[PDB]
Image (spheres, rainbow, N blue to C red):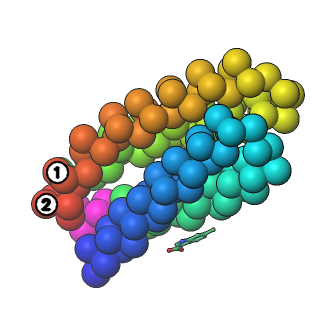
Amino acid sequence: SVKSEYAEAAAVGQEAVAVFNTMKAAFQNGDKEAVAQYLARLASLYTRHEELLNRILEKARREGNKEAVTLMNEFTATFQTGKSIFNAMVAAFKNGDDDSFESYLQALEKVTAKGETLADQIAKAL
Ligand SMILES: Cc1ccc2c(C(=O)O)c[nH]c2c1
């Protein structure tokens, strides 16, 4: 059901947290080859996460589940902010701008946390 889809979306989000934290450690340690691979894997994880979120939102709309639709619209808007920040982080890595990369790492953590505040209301709405 939409809940098994929620559970997979939540798990993909958690996988991205895990890989992000490994990548932050690799960035701090100066292991650029690792950072490159973790960024590629994060890109794939965020693409999958977005796919699942869109299926959940479309299913909620087709059900006419107004509260789930509202929460999912809010969550996905914050998710898109995070993706913009992620993209900027990737560009800072490409450009060799470690100062900006550090800053974006911090911003992405805060934007991710902002969206997660909605997750527990989403689960009970769907
Ligand atoms: C790179 C990648 C892509 C998709 C998934 C996934 C999923 O589709 O549920 C779980 N971990 C992943 C990791």
One can see residue 105 in this view: yes
The structure residue drawn at horizontal position 68% and vertical position 39%, both measured from the top left corner, is 29
Say the numbered circle drawn on residue 58: none
Front residue (pair 24, 73): 24
Image quadrant holding the N terminus, namely bottom left
Amino acid beneath label 1:
Gln
- Secondary-structure class at tag 2: helix
- Disc 1, disc 2: CB below 8 Å? yes
Say the numbered circle drawn on residue 124: 2
User: What range is drawn magenta here?
Assistant: 60-64
Q: Is mark 1 within 8 Å of ligand 1?
A: no
Residue placed farthest to the left in the image?
A: 124
Horizontal and vertical percent for residue 116?
Answer: 31, 45
Image quadrant holding the C terminus, namely bottom left
The structure residue drawn at horizontal position 26% and vertical position 73%, both measured from the top left corner, is 3
Residue placed farthest to the right in the image?
A: 95
Q: Is residue 102 above or below residue 21?
A: above
Q: Is residue 114 above or below residue 15?
A: above
Q: Is mark 2 within 8 Å of ligand 1?
A: no
Front residue (pair 33, 111): 33
CA gap between label 1 and label 2 equals 5 Å
Q: Residues within 10 Å of mark 1 (few under 14, many from 20)?
A: some
Q: Is residue 80 left or right of residue 64?
A: right
Quarter assignment of residue 93: top right
Query: Which residue is denoted by mark 1 in the rendering?
Result: 121
Q: Is residue 126 left or right of residue 5?
A: left
Horizontal and vertical percent for residue 114?
Answer: 33, 34
Amino acid beneath label 2:
Lys
Quarter assignment of residue 89: top right
Quarter assignment of residue 9: bottom left
Q: Quadrant of ligand 1?
A: bottom right
The structure residue drawn at horizontal position 47% and vertical position 52%, both measured from the top left corner, is 17
